Image (cartoon, rainbow, N blue to C red; front, side, top):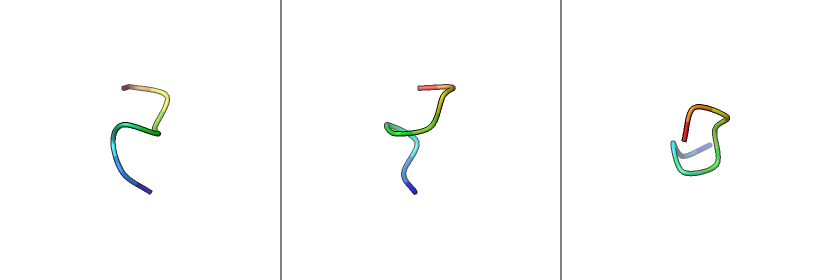
Length: 9
């Protein structure tokens, strides 16, 4: 669950 996939990024 990387940041690039998160809703924030």
